[PDB]
Amino acid sequence: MVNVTVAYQTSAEPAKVAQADNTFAKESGATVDWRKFDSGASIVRALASGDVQIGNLGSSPLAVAASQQVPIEVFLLASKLGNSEALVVKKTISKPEDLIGKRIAVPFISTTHYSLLAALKHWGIKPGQVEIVNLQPPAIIAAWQRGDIDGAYVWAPAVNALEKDGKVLTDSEQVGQWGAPTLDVWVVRKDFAEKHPEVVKAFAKSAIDAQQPYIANPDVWLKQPENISKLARLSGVPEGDVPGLVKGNTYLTPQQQTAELTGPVNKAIIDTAQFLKEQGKVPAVANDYSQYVTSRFV
Image 1 (cartoon, rainbow, N blue to C red):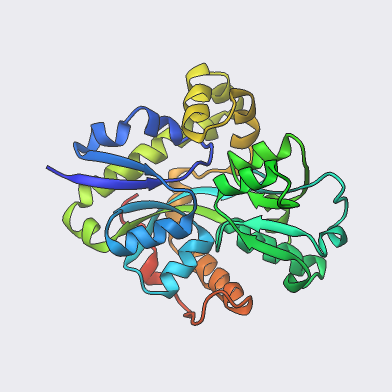
Image 2 (cartoon, helix red, strand yellow):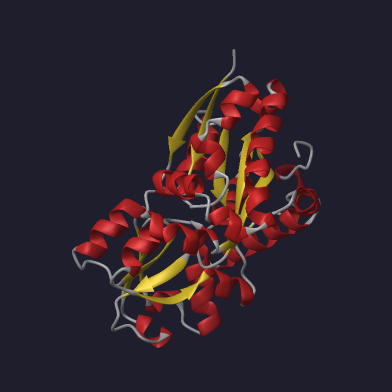
């Protein structure tokens, strides 16, 4: 009897179909407690305490966790982030220079915190010129509704909630093109991987299998109504928003998973940590994070 707690986040992406179908529990035989978390930083804390054994992290919280020597490994990429993550602002903010003096919310050290800082640097705006405030996405939505912030760099469901009456100023496809790409990954605690390697393998299988039909033909995948409804439910977004969100990232074949986990993810962590250090968010970083990545479960 295996019990495993999986920390998940709200991105609308094809592997949510396997989550809704309970495929991981069915194939692994484990009792799975799927726990929704509002951002990666809170997942890092739950991984470090042992309350969570498998967790979905943005690349920015991943780099923070690895720089603190949390005993976790990336064993699977979830997505390469594009415009599914975006900076949405009040409609009177028309140009990046209009961000000066404004109150912009991001969840602390999320991929969108990282991308906001990378976007400001690319634009030549110092982060001290913007009032950057840290709120979790439910609080961001509530503060936006009451007019207490001028914008936020967010993912679903906050990104589409804000965009209904706001404007997109930049997004993570653009910030990636400017040289600061972000990723979503799955990580596992070493002690869990040591005791239940076949359960970890079954998690990776369930996620990879769910994404391949989308990769093969996005438009055919998106017209299967149960694919849309399952993502709408788990992400908390209207069905009409799901296709745009799903198309806002790219996903990996099994060959691409093995390729990325054998070098590129390490390099991504190295660079992400270095930028976070330069922005004053992490005190110490390493020049190699190979301890934090593995291909052995795919």
